[PDB]
Image (cartoon, helix red, strand yellow):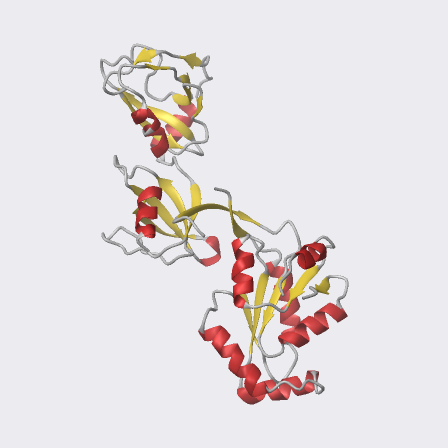
Length: 334
């Protein structure tokens, strides 16, 4: 390789184009792929392979390729442009060797139908790593990598860009495309338990490990729950699906564990072992569980098949609470 030269600063009159095709993106930065042969551009410092850092004092460092070229479209004809540039042949070789320019993650919030074999369909919820923001030489269509099982990079497709995406969203909270990153809770997370012994779990955990656990005094009232988090203690909560959907909204992501009853009689065998005082019908508890399951399991993060013969649940519960707590989640950044 070689060392970098001094930082260029440049003034030249825009014709009916600045005469500049670009490579790059946000992570590697916005570079010049080419100068228009004969241009006012080329009359200055701007050869192939320089990075564009600034324009009319505008931050080109944290800026997607697409919404570079538009900023370079917008600029009135026959007007001055004041680009602050640096060569960086080291960063550009990499670009041309492996294209890589754009890299950010976007969580979807609307269904889409694929209208071309390379396109990707997607429910609301599907996170995508966006890697191209002018697919080939075109506005409208981004390149993307599908993100599914344990956050892997699984399928390489093309999707509608952010604005088109909101159109198709509009003809139907949440953009069409949220921009998100991966984080672990900087705090202990509220816990939400479901299934026919859920009330015994809150009982047991909260009592038998009263150091880590505290049942939030109820209905939601999350100053009950913050004033519980503040204490490095898990907010055990008896709440509902909407009540959860809502806490998702705020990115206060709880852990939602589902204790899946094995059988109708199962429940009875179990509740009898653990709470003979309880007056609550097993039929009624089983029946609930399945509605809650049949309608929206999008709630529960992790689930646990109660084995009615024992109380292994209690263990595999602790485990899961304490291994989800070590789980990276998606959170917003806009």
